């Protein structure tokens, strides 16, 4: 298992990161029951870095996850999660029964002046290791880092922009280097596009991107090289992206993606399907 | 296009009803609002807003969008000491509706505190009818038995009247005895009876997954999608007033409407129940 420093953060994070797939909805019990075993498996097999944002919100799930994490040693895992935002961090820290969060990041106006300062105060207190931000659009990330105070934002998290099908994050990597920001990729598979089963029912991806990615998955199938294996291989394949956050419930998926990323990537196959995904490279569906 | 009566409640629900589904929840949101508009346009009055209760921003958008449709043209339902009454109040407040048609309860002794409270809210005329929601029919039976009489008007249940599971059948005589309307849900087994297949999180055992995949590719070779047969079967029983499917895009809603309005091939249902053999009613809860 390979590790990267998360920018100027000091945390050695594994090139893949477990994101604890969404638990809300009916059958939530099954999903969180499996997610606990997945946390254990990811830690036992190399993933320091667990994000539990989907647990941010559910009293009982968060508390028995606090039990589960109390089963694990102090330095055995790095944990990150999502005016009154101070009390929110305090509240959910109590529910997790952890004594301090390794990194807090803001979901989503001028978060620049209200939430981020409170989290900076919290980092000075000793209860939060580092601060970061989460968003969909890289222009928004640039905006908020720009108008914030210097060296406030230590990490950024962003979705579907370093894949076989989307390449945008490159354009911003330099910028992050210039302001000392660790980069966290997420959704390596394009949320179904780089899957061999296909794309979920809610996915609004245009018909063209859908067809390009389905044909790439078919070519991968015919070459005996699963498209998801290639996608997860590729999202952790950039030395400037410290880590990528994949979401799953069953521990089998954690172990499969571990086995994938630890196996050598086929750069010729990357060239091939990046070609087959034609005009649809960096086509957006947000 | 076909309507039945929800037990004795006097609400006329279509055989198929829309249960709008679950980062990336805003995109699902907008699509789901368009989907409820499409469904109400095509006759699917029964609208369950349970996944919106919990996010102020999420319930507000459907409240404001739904204000654009006539009140008598749709029947609405949602999820829920007497904190339940305050929950109903606030749900109406963000949905900007003066009357909820059906109010349900998820999940121990809700028979003496929660259900009497919701009954009181019905007495006042804010809610029309009161029901319960569970994955286990035994738990539904317990609640109905131990509750005050004629309290439980609706019972919602998942993955127990479909091509692979029909454990709801055994309880239908009971539900008729009690005066309880039945709302089926998840007619696809949450991916089993789909051509694409099962999500990663699904716990269903190897044998069930394989039998359903074989039935699926058989349906494919026959030119008759497994999803069409699934939704047709689920709505095919007259003692089950309505079946609730959770979709996001409006195209799925239109597909399912066209599917239920097509006749069902019972020979195909039996050829599929032969592929789903010892796996019928195998639980994964």
Image (cartoon, coloured by chain):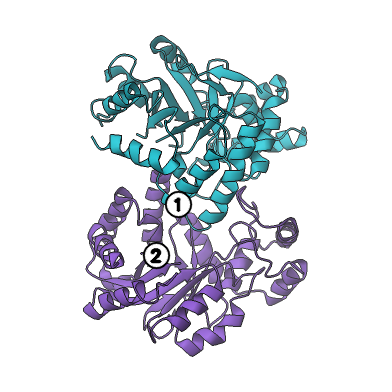
Chain colours: A cyan, B purple
Pointer 2 chain: B
Label placed on residue B114:
none
Q: Is residue A202 visible?
A: yes
Residue sticking out furthest to the top: A178
Q: Report how many numbered discs are placed on residues in the image.
A: 2
- Number of other residues with Cα within 10 Å of mark 1, as a class: few under 14, some 14 to 19, many 20 or more: few
Relative placement, left or right, of A50 versus B60 is right
What residue is rendered at 22% in x and 68% in y? B98
Q: Quadrant of residue A115?
A: top left
Relative placement, left or right, of A281 versus B20 is right
Label 1, on which residue?
A60
Looking at the rendered image, the quarter that the N terminus of chain A falls into is top right
Looking at the rendered image, the quarter that the C terminus of chain A falls into is top left
Pointer 1 chain: A
Position in image of residue B58 (x %, y %): 33, 50
Q: Quadrant of residue A223?
A: top right
Q: Quadrant of residue B103?
A: bottom left
Residues at circles 2 and 1 in contact by the CB criterion of under 8 Å: no
Mark 2 or 1: the one toward you: 1
Asked which secondary structure carries label 1, the reply is helix
The vertical placement of B69 against B161, above or below, is: above
Label placed on residue B48:
2
Position in image of residue B31 (x %, y %): 41, 50
Q: CA distance from mark 2 to mark 1?
A: 25 Å
Asked which secondary structure carries label 2, the reply is strand
Position in image of residue B116 (x %, y %): 32, 77
Badge 2 and badge 1 both on one subunit: no
Observer-nearest of A136 and A7: A7
What residue is rendered at 30% in x and 17% in y? A146
Observer-nearest of A283 and A80: A80
- Number of other residues with Cα within 10 Å of mark 2, as a class: few under 14, some 14 to 19, many 20 or more: many
Position in image of residue B274 (x %, y %): 77, 71
């Amino acid at each position: 298992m390979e590790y990267r420093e998360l920018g100027k953060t000091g945390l050695k994070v594994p090139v893949l990161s477990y994101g604890a797939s969404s638990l809300g909805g009916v059958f939530h019990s099954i999903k969180e029951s499996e997610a606990i075993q997945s946390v254990f498996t990811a830690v036992e097999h190399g993933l320091n870095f667990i994000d539990v944002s989907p647990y941010y919100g559910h009293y009982k799930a968060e508390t028995v996850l606090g039990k589960a994490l109390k089963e694990l040693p102090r330095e055995s895992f790095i944990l990150s999660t999502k005016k009154r935002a101070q009390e929110s961090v305090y509240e959910s820290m109590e529910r997790l029964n952890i004594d301090h969060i390794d990194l807090i990041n803001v979901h989503d106006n001028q978060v620049v002046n209200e939430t981020l300062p409170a989290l900076v105060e919290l980092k000075e207190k000793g209860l939060v290791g580092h601060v970061g931000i989460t968003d969909l659009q890289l222009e928004n990330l640039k905006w908020v880092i720009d108008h914030a105070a210097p060296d406030t934002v230590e990490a950024v998290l962003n979705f579907c922009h370093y894949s076989l099908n989307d390449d945008k994050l490159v354009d911003f990597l330099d910028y992050f280097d210039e302001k000392g920001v660790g980069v966290i990729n997420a959704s390596p598979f394009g949320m179904g596009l780089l899957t061999q089963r296909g794309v979920p029912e809610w996915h609004p991806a245009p018909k063209s991107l859908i067809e390009a990615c389905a044909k790439a998955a078919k070519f991968c199938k015919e070459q005996g090289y699963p498209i998801e294996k290639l996608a997860v291989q590729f999202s952790v394949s950039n030395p400037r992206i410290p880590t990528t956050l994949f979401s799953s419930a069953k521990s089998e998926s954690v172990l499969q993606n571990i086995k994938y990323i630890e196996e050598p990537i086929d750069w010729s196959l990357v060239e091939k399907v990046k070609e087959i995904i034609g005009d649809q490279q960096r086509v957006s569906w947000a």
